[PDB]
Image: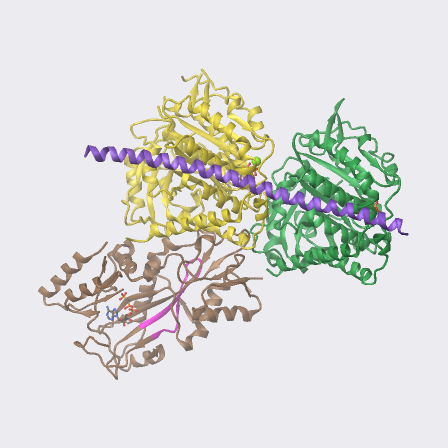
Amino acid sequence: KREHEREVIQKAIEENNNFIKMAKEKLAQKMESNKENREAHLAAMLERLQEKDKHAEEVRKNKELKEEAS
Amino acid sequence: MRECISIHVGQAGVQIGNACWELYCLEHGIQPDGQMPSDDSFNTFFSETGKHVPRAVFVDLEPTVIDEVRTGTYRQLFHPEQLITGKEDAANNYARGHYTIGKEIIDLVLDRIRKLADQCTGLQGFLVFHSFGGGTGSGFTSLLMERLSVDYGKKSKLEFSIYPAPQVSTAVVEPYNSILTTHTTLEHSDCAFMVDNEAIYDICRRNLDIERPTYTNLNRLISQIVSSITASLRFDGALNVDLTEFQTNLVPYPRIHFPLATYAPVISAEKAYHEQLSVAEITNACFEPANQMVKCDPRHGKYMACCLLYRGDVVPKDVNAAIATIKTKRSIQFVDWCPTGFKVGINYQPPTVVPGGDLAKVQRAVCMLSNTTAIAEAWARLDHKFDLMYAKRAFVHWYVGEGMEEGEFSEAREDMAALEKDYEEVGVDS
Amino acid sequence: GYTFVVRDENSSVYAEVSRLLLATGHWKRLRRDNPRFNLMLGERNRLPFGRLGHEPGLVQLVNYYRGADKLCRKASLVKLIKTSPELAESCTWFPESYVIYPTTDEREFFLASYNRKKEDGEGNVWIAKSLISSEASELLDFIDNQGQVHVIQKYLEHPLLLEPGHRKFDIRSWVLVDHQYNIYLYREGVLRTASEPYHVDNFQDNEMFFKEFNQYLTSALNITLESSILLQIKHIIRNCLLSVEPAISTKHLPYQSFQLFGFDFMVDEELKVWLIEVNGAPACAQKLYAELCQGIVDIAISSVFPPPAAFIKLENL
Amino acid sequence: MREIVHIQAGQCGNQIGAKFWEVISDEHGIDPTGSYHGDSDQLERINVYYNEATGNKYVPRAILVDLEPGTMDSVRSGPFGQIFRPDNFVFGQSGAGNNWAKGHYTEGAELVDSVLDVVRKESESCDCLQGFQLTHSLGGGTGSGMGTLLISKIREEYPDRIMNTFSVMPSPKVSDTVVEPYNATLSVHQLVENTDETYCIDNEALYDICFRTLKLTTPTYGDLNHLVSATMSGVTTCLRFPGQLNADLRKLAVNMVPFPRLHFFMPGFAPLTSRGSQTVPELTQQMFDSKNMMAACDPRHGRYLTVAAIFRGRMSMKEVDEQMLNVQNKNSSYFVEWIPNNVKTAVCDIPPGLKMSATFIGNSTAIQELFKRISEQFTAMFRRKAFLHWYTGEGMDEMEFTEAESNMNDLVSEYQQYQDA
Ligand SMILES: Nc1nc2c(ncn2[C@@H]2O[C@H](COP(=O)(O)OP(=O)(O)OP(=O)(O)O)[C@@H](O)[C@H]2O)c(=O)[nH]1
Ligand SMILES: Nc1ncnc2c1ncn2[C@@H]1O[C@H](COP(=O)(O)OP(=O)(O)CP(=O)(O)O)[C@@H](O)[C@H]1O
Ligand SMILES: Nc1nc2c(ncn2[C@@H]2O[C@H](COP(=O)(O)OP(=O)(O)O)[C@@H](O)[C@H]2O)c(=O)[nH]1
Ligand SMILES: [Mg+2]
């Protein structure tokens, strides 16, 4: 019976500690994966805007070509 | 020696917190400067210096609202470190409150909370006040609850959650924030008292004759119900029963931790008439749907617990006689697996009202805390509104834009579907 | 304007009611889960009553009274008769019944009553429903060999038999309870008759209307349908709906309710009416569908959403 | 503080922008010298639009942009011309000739970097910048082409901020150049992608309001701008005064925009006209009426995704709530059922001007009628390649026109999809 009394209290510790452990790791994983997702959304947004600038440089150059071949 | 730290998150939590602490001060004879001439049970909520200071922390991602506390009548009451503010709010977005902006202020909050915990010789737990609809109230609170479960493992965490009502709603995405916060906080909350703003609004219009109630009107009535619930922790007596003892009876299953609160009497300060109101009258009012904190029909829901918390001139004889009459006359049906009995608590300290308030001062009052499956109607209403919008993915881009995924939406909704099913199962006979 | 939803396609009664609303020009039918409705013709099980009357400005009415199943389910009706203060001591019209659970549980009380009847030489035939026998040992075994809760009711061994044919019958009455709780008994009833002669030993075994039944009563017993059966029926309906009235009343609820009920009666040879069962979602007789469904549209729907003599309003004295 | 950086570009942008500043400066008790001489507590949220300068002066956080000095010389001389920061005036000498390509790619590209230097300076001096608001027209060249260019560059530098615009749509009834449908289509293509919320101010609607109802035979730009300033004051009320509903640009966007592309609002105002002029139920019925919309669309031809109503002046809040519930329910078919409680209401004690007024902001699917009108006009010219040489001569390709036309047609089909849901 003393053997079981020690198994009960150790089971309670192992469960609370393991719960605290999992929650800590899952929260850090969520905050990290969120950071990655938000930064990816901004990176794609800026990539789209940059592709638009590259196109404006190509338009200004396309005018430079037409003016010289006039 | 069991202290209780209160945490007020977002506008609703802060403004409700202001009302509760204003009431607690009046109840304990504490002046706005912290001085208490009458000077213990009230030390569960107040630390001493002869200044009595609330064991509370006010958190908001924007400074207007807390700045009113910092400059208001009770500015002296709180220590500056207890009032924490950010610069940019969560814009009614759970994702901003939990992730984008929450990450920036969380550690500071946990430190200010740690400073209160360090002054406790035997911390009992936390009382978290917040709205379901706001970005901070929903998002930041669930992050806070997640971190508190880590930093304070065992400790109990109770909630006072402000359920959204269209009459006073400020955002179309409140259903989203409500499901998201409920899902995330479910494992981390031991007991949650939902306060339906629509129910408090309708009581103010009916019982107080207020044409268009304001937050001040709502919050003062809310503070009375919150006071009744926490009275057992701030006072002590032979007939006083501790809230944690009621909590053992109130929560049969970890997930079914949402008691319905009903309060009586709510009488207008001008239309008081001088009527006294027997123990029998107020006890009967606890079973009138018009007096519940959440809109639902308990007549068509099975009870798992029923607790009566009396506050003024009340003697057991009257209580037992009132309960006897209520039985064999009311639709009080318990689940076949729970004893059909009422747990009673009496605090001889009469109810206090704010001078120049809408509520009349009464000789006796009662708050009933009952765990009824009827509260699941509130989840059904919220889940239906979530379903209407989520079907079209309306507004979801605002959440995804802050790093969230559609997966969290369906995961939170599936958990709510399971919760609605749990309330259904617990009502079925064995 | 007025809009309505249909969440029960199997309901034959409300399918006709839906057609009548659409015929007026005042009613438009919305999709199943559109929550901006005025009238809801809801589903039989798990109707979302909690979501009703919460959309601001809208007046919402539902074709069912939340609860009422406490009067309709066999076990809950037995529980209501034996426990309601309004019925426990006054009920003389419900056959002696005991709720028997297979896997609370009035098994010991049934055996005490069964033994009282066999000792005194009294009639001991009982009917188990979720088997007709005079043994109780084979009646109890029948219940235990099923995963359902049954009710052991006293079998009416001496019923009123229709001549010619010498046959058993039961009466079905349609009752419409509108918002504000006004009980209306539909003028026309139906007799679900048997087409075989009655036997007091063989335990192994067609719609007559009130005009033909009234004509059989005089000449057969020289008595009319009223003063012998119709007064009893009206009394039973009034007592049953008013016992559950405080538990189902929508006066303190954000929405309004109305319901059509199907009361089932059985007349004994002494002309005494006995309530057998109440139906929450009843089915009408083919010729009475047009009049009954129009009565539901006028009394229950048009009273709440505004654009004869066939429904007797039941009142006391 | 939650600051907004205001930018006004081109003739229209600077004319409506100057009026907006005169209107709100009056409402906030700020005189042309920048000094405060009001009552109440104006001033509580003055920092949303105003910087605090030496000597207790409030300076509008506005940037004035144009490729021609003309309109800029008119401002700086008119009323409230001396209120602006002189350094914030950024102009060129060669205009844009009502050519989007010139404003977006050539003339505008030469001036854009110097504008961004002023934007950056104003942003660095913000405790917490909420975003930017741009006033401009879509039919000209500077406001249309260079304005959309500015939006693109600002978004690159501030991707996490809100981009709001007041965009004046062109109309044949009030036109100056035949190439307006080209400029407008090209600008709408940009706005669809790079703004969070756009207030569609239609010159066709402003004209029809002045002409029909107001009974003005020949309305001038001054007559049209009176409607714009009254609307702009109204739609910005919740941002300038202490409130709960849509208090900032982000909260407004979160409440008004269910789908990222569908962010084009249809403003409304009541009662119509001041410019020398003279109940709650009357205010409500008018603000929801097609005749009071600043976009030439019939709301009864579509459905409202979201709506924001604002009432100004002393009135019964109980009556406001009753009336708003009455417009819904009586017209419940014109509000999408799949967005619960999509109509929000705010009330401000301080009226404009008038004793009491109402302002309507709606995200209606009927807004497709505006984009259809432009698309029809764009196609009538593009089909016959009319005047394309002015745009191709600046470096642009025909493919760019086909993409802008297609993106706007997609926008219309998206608005129709949600109308049939
Ligand atoms: N009873 C009551 N409800 C309130 C109060 N303040 C806000 N609410 C409700 O709470 C919800 C909005 O949450 P808020 O608390 O305003 O938001 P927040 O937590 O500050 O979040 P963000 O502003 O988005 O950062 C709505 O349902 C409001 O009706 C208050 O003082 N009392
Ligand atoms: N006590 C009784 N005496 C005589 N006939 C009975 C009876 N109980 C039931 N019956 C007959 O058996 C049929 C069984 O019908 P059903 O199974 O739908 O329920 P019911 O109306 O009998 C319910 P209850 O359990 O309340 O008696 C009845 O329609 C009736 O004809
Ligand atoms: N409402 C209004 N429209 C204007 C005003 N000025 C110009 N417009 C419109 O703007 C368009 C012409 O572009 P404009 O802004 O003048 O030139 P830009 O400098 O090239 O942007 C046309 O559709 C005009 O109707 C003004 O002050 N008010
Ligand atoms: Mg807030």
Q: Position of residue C255 (x, y in %)?
A: 47, 54
* Residue under the point 63% across and 59% down: D417
Q: Looking at this rendering, what residue extends furthest in the top direction? A: B50
| Colour chosen for chain D | green
Q: Which residues are magenta?
A: C171-190
Magenta stretch, main secondary structure, is strand
Q: Percent x, y for residue D136?
A: 78, 44
* Quadrant housing the N terminus of chain A: top left
Q: Judge from the rendering whether residue C92 lies leftward or rightward of residue D211; answer left or right.
A: left
Residue D413 can be seen in this image: yes
| Chain A, hue in figure | purple
Colour of chain B as rendered: yellow
> x%, y% of residue D142?
82, 44
Picture quadrant of residue C68: bottom left
Furthest residue in direction left, as rendered: C119
In the picture, which chain is brown?
Answer: C
Residue closer to the observer: B96 or B331: B96
